Length: 118
Length: 118
Image 1 (cartoon, rainbow over the protein chains, first blue to last red):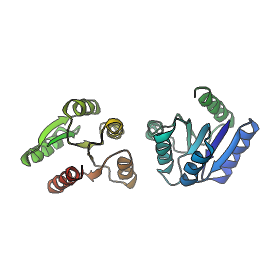
Image 2: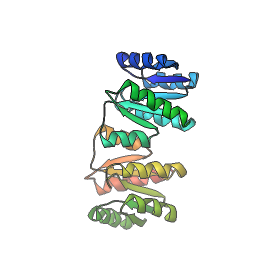
Image 3: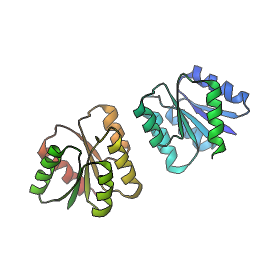
């Protein structure tokens, strides 16, 4: 299956890409909200891992605009861990929301769970 | 025209109701997000003044769920005045966002402007 990893930090993108590859997923990457929508349209990923941050609001907007056309599963990843943050991510269309720093094994388990149910 | 005023503080609702009545609008009021959706469905207001606060997220949700079915103009009113707050209110479907405390004359002017363009 194909995963699009949207992350504006190259070090974190690289860790998730490495771990997802090791599980047998094909990985496409995007580093801002524009590349995220472009890759979403062109690559039709089976799931999207979306960090909230490039700048504060762009992840939420990416998820919002994807949801206009597609039910593709979205797992939001973010250092922001407040109730507001989690609640708003989910209400705007994320299927899950995981905080950083995260466990690589838990992330894999959550991606699997999302793909099973979709 | 008919305005639905959604405000969880009775003193502020009463001021807006008084001022809107004085301009010749018919006013319906709601005091939480449940009553807001109920009144929206039953009364079909021409415009909605929505305060963000009952609890923090419910105004945003009200606007979000109204926008599933209707293009009715929404003016959000809130003591929260940060960039994030204004930006997220508008992205979730508000047509305008006005901070409290507000000028009664400016509010009237903004309601008129919204109704003209709708």
